[PDB]
Image: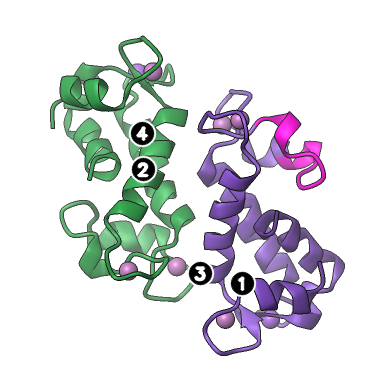
Chain colours: A purple, B green
Amino acid sequence: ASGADALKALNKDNDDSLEIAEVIHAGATTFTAINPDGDTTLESGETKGRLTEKDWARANKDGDQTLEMDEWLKILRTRFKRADANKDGKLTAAELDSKAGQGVLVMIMK
Amino acid sequence: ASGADALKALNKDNDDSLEIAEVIHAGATTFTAINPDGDTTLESGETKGRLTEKDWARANKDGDQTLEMDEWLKILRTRFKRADANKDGKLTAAELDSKAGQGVLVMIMK
Ligand SMILES: [La+3]
Ligand SMILES: [La+3]
Ligand SMILES: [La+3]
Ligand SMILES: [La+3]
Ligand SMILES: [La+3]
Ligand SMILES: [La+3]
Ligand code: NA
Ligand code: NA
């Protein structure tokens, strides 16, 4: 999806950017949206096309084979900061359209 | 609540302990449940009896006045490790009955 697409679906506060509260919340809903087996965790087979193998290495450090909500969202907040080019806490459509911004979108839109 | 109370209410996998996947899930459910004003965040007035001001200082470092899902769960995972006395990844009723374990329960039981 484009940055304009993401703003159409997720932005509700009469601006033209996504902030950390909007991004984390959408990331939490997407966590549930991509979990179809009825448990409470994400496995490597459920994150294909959204997380890489190295993403699991930097987030999953408790020794298990499961991604909990906080581990999932920690990757998201890091991608948020990587896409925040001018570091103002807001992600415009142009910032969401960057290669780093696209990494945010795959975690907040199913 | 006591450790035995928490296991009866929250433990579903036929053991005698709460693991990190079960704790994070109940903490995520509690986050939404104790948020009555219709937004997606927790404010300081909504975490009374569960978090202290120093908890906000160590978790809320993005400069706002709101606690997002990942900031809330980050406090919880730290409390989990503080309560995991033998560091085996499981919280028994006895560990949930300690001072550190009660800090876990106030974040996973509304
Ligand atoms: La906004
Ligand atoms: La799953
Ligand atoms: La994990
Ligand atoms: La258990
Ligand atoms: La609130
Ligand atoms: La915050
Ligand atoms: Na920005
Ligand atoms: Na333990």
Judge from the rendering whether residue A78 lies leftward or rightward of residue B34; answer left or right: right
User: Residue tagged by mark 1?
Assistant: A10
Q: Which residue is mark 3?
A: A21
Residue placed under numbered mark 4 in the picture: B80
Q: Which residue is mark 2?
A: B27
Residue occupying the point 25% across, 21% down: B7
* Residue extent of the magenta highlight: A43-55
Q: Is residue B41 above or below residue B20?
A: below
Query: As shown in the figure, which amino acid type bears the numbered disc 2?
Result: Gly
Residue depicted at 79% across the width and 39% down the height: A48
- Identified at 73% across, 39% down, the residue is A47
Report the front residue among A48 and A82: A48
Ligand 4 falls in quadrant: top left
- Per the model, the C-alpha gap separating discs 2 and 1 is 24 Å
Side of A94 relative to B65 (left or right):
right
Chain bearing mark 2 = B
